[PDB]
Image: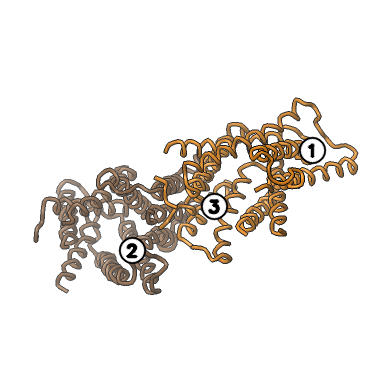
Chain colours: A brown, B orange
Amino acid sequence: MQWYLVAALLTILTSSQGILTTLSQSATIPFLAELFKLSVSGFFLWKECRTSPSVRMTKEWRSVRLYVVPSVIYLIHNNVQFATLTYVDPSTYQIMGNLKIVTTGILFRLVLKRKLSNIQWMAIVLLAVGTTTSQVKGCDSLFSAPLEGYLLGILSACLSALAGVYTEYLMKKNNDSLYWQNVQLYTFGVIFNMGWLIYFNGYSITTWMVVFNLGSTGLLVSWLMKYSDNIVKVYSTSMAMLLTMVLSIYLFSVKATIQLFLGIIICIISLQMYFMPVHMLIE
Amino acid sequence: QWYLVAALLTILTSSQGILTTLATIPFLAELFKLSVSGFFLWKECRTSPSVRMTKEWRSVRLYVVPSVIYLIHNNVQFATLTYVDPSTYQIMGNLKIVTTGILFRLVLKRKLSNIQWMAIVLLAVGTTTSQVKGCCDSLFPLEGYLLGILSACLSALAGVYTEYLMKKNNDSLYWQNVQLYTFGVIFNMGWLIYGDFKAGFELGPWWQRLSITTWMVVFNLGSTGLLVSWLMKYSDNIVKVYSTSMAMLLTMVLSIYLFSVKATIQLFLGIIICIISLQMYFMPVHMLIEL
């Protein structure tokens, strides 16, 4: 129940689905992954009602209706992601993607109205810069894309951030049960995943592993949306992507570069800056 | 004010950068520093009633050391380049930032916060990032890496030891310069004699053989060198290496508007790292925590 252990586990599992996704490289995963979160949340909700004297649960449409929004944002986001890739090569797209770190940062302050120090603001930026540094191409063509590409890449990041920030709003706007908030959230996700398909096929063990892993990480993200903040999330995600590159060296035997070494140092420092207690920062 | 000197050093360290692309001068550059220091020393003795000056060999002898280190350093620099390409050598050079950092604490026994230590590292990381070979490419023998490292330690030791000399006395800047740059002139001159000996003196008469652009860099190299001494006395090595490092960034950014050279994201990124590394080190710790 310690936020850092959840955050650490999210890091471990965000990089697990990273590797397990590639290992199954020679579609309806998101659908199965949603139902896994919805059915595991439902289970704990039901179990909590049967085990516990009191469970706080707002059934009023005033608040339940708002769990649509994340799904609507994520739907629009996925169209923008697809749109972007038709103007930019994947690496240009991948590196514009580190802007979600700063856009979550900004909306954290604007929408969630939480305050950050100067040292913290410098850490948010350093994280984005440190991740980008690691992804710079070890010795493609960015700076060559149409304006549409650059503008969409940016709007993609804003939607990504908005979805996460709005979810935190939903969790923290009530003193309701985590499991009941999940059940509403993941109900609309199931509905929308299904509406998309309305708008197996070699399913291996490996395939089932990523469905579980994608479900797992998603429940942790919700936990952190409730009992911790978006910035903790994006530090977990970002450290996952660094670990993925470090694990790719020992497994898929990919070329370690100086930009990986540098980006890790930047990120480790960006971690300390943001999460350091301000008495420790000052010796 | 130290920051204006530091800013001027940045401006002039990038000037000699450009003017270079447009090497006996070390001798003329030292002679310029020795003769400009001598002038101010003489003028200070004629103008002020007392000028502090330690003439005792106990302390005067210690101005040899920098020259001995710099001599050894130049041999190591040359030695290194025979194992690694220019670029690998250029990027190993950012280690002087951390070695000055360490010796600042060890030799100069000065205090650095955690935030400051993180800034020293960030500066080295930020400069490296701007240099790092994008899309000529032979990083990733040990001699090379070990000598590159030893080079940085000596570089740092020379700078840190000079600061020690300036700040070990409450003597005049101009008298400290005059001792420092006397040994430099002597050694520069011994080297030029050696170099002529190496080719049997067979070229034009050594004493006789001793553009405008050429004169610009001699002055420019002299100028920056006097500023470094000022900062060794009334400022620290870390301010120096921030000035140098920002010069190397400026040089790359100025090369884009002048020589129209290849702008990369690594330049953009390294600047942001460095800007942030600047704030971290030179920010007052109450400002670092304000909203």
Q: Amino acid at mark 2?
A: Ser
Residue A197, image x and y in percent? 15, 69
Q: Quadrant of residue A251?
A: top left
Q: Of helix, strand and loop, which one carries label 1?
A: helix
Q: Which residue is mark 1?
A: B175
Q: Which residue is mark 3?
A: B290
Q: Which label sits in the foreground, 2 or 1?
A: 1
Q: Nearer the viewer, residue B248 or B258?
A: B258
Please give left or right for residue B190 compared with residue A75 in the image.
right
**Eyeballing the image, is B92 above or below A233?**
above
Q: Of helix, strand and loop, which one carries label 2?
A: helix
Q: Of helix, strand and loop, which one carries label 3?
A: loop
Residue B50, image x and y in percent? 88, 37
Q: Nearer the viewer, residue B282 or A256?
A: A256
Q: Amino acid at mark 3?
A: Glu
Chain letter for mark 3, please.
B
Q: Which residue is mark 2?
A: A160
